[PDB]
Amino acid sequence: GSSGSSGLRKAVEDYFCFCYGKALGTTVMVPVPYEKMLRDQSAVVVQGLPEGVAFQHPENYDLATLKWILENKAGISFIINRPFLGPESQLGGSGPSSG
Image 1: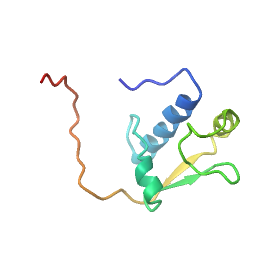
Image 2: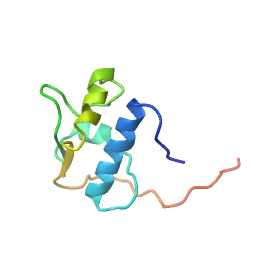
Image 3: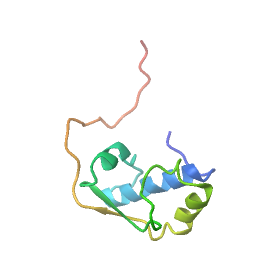
Image 4: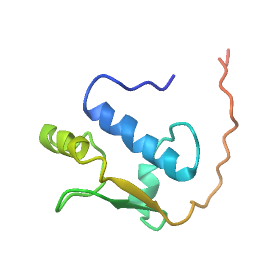
């Protein structure tokens, strides 16, 4: 499944999602499409970050920053502007594919 409680880096990730999910208007967690945002920032905007700090993967953020983001997450907000484009649907359901 998709859990996230222990650890910091993850926590930051588990959070960022909750945001996107809260922005999307869902009641679950969404996998922040970094590659997307990274590639083009004309989809989702980031607000509430530290000076001279992007929303880049947290895995990079220094143990300090990571804690910073968390210490200033209430300020972090995903300013949605528009959805993404391209071939992608993904059905809602998981199953063990044998073979």
